[PDB]
Amino acid sequence: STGSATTTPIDSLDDAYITPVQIGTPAQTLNLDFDTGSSDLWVFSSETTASEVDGQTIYTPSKSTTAKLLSGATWSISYGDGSSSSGDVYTDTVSVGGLTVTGQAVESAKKVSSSFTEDSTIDGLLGLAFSTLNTVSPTQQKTFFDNAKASLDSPVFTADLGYHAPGTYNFGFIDTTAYTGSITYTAVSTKQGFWEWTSTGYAVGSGTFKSTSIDGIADTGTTLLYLPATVVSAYWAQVSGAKSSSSVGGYVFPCSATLPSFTFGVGSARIVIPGDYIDFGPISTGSSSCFGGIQSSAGIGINIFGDVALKAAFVVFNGATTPTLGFASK
């Protein structure tokens, strides 16, 4: 089997991407944030505290003839940005882009934190990291990809995120028309539960490439590119007037600036992030200070190749017995 679904930016900045997902029978379509940095499929639901729902579409398990309470199971997750959610668990049929999994754990939110309530466009998350990070207790549950893997033509999914445009998540096949040149594959460590890999270096604009190992994760659920402070300082030093602002929470730059590109290495290959992908616009409406899309990881504990990086590439998440990542230009 295979599946193919369009993923669409939630706003004009590409702050996140939503993909329609069919849950239950008859189908209830919810727009979920596919997140290669977590491993829970959780949704706003008929069980979510009413004051914490503000415009999201909800899953109502009692209206699904295939829903079954997973007795005794609870979940609770806290994300790297400080947000969180928790609840109970049903199993139900879940389909993405024509690919159907029966018996998928659908984690129904009883509580969500403010940032989720305040985003009416995201009806939940679909985690695509390794199932060892799934938070369901006392019986850990498998991700959608893990459940689908054996049925797929090839044990892979691909992320082709658009810049200010829709893109595609494919499951079970690699669309050879979706990228240019060749895909370069690189080793993955699953020891932390992430799609963790080592970039071979970077360049700023037309500058020389610096060969250096940068360990990080490929994370579709993180908006920006978080890298070591040395790298980030080298980038923003090429933008006149750019500075790190403690009050804003990162590097800002004059909105009148033209940003240089940023290149990262994948083995001997190179992925170029155009400067325009690094512009996240005014820090507040009407401001002439703009927020940068490359930020320091120094306070995170891990480097994160988020959407800013991933949207410059066609990315293969190879879930073979020994997983690998592939990157191609496009």
Image: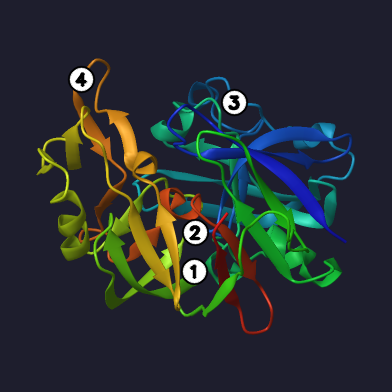
Instruction: Look at the numbered discs 3 and 1 and tell me whether their residues touch, using CB distance below 8 Å.
Output: no
Q: Residue furthest front?
A: 206
Task: Please give the residue where the numbered disc 2 appears in the rendered image.
Answer: 37
Q: Dot 2: what SS?
A: loop
Q: Amino acid at mark 1?
A: Phe
Q: Nearer the viewer, mark 4 or mark 1?
A: 4
Instruction: Relative to 19, say whether 301 is above or below.
Output: below
Circle number at residue 194: 1
Instruction: Look at the numbered discs 4 and 1 and tell me whether their residues touch, using CB distance below 8 Å.
Output: no
Q: Earlier in the sequence, mark 3 or mark 2?
A: 2
Give the crowd class for mark 1: few <14, some 14-19, many >=20 residues within 10 Å. many
Residue 21 is situated, as x and y percent measured from the top left of the image, at: 73, 41
Give the crowd class for mark 3: few <14, some 14-19, many >=20 residues within 10 Å. many
Q: Nearer the viewer, mark 3 or mark 4?
A: 4
Q: Quadrant of residue 212?
A: bottom left
Q: Amino acid at mark 4?
A: Ser
Observer-nearest of 271 and 66: 271
User: Gap between marks 3 and 1, in whole Å?
Assistant: 28 Å
Task: Please give the residue where the numbered disc 3 appears in the rendered image.
Answer: 56
Q: Dot 1: what SS?
A: loop
Instruction: Look at the numbered discs 1 and 2 and tell me whether their residues touch, using CB distance below 8 Å.
Output: yes
Q: Quadrant of residue 213?
A: bottom left
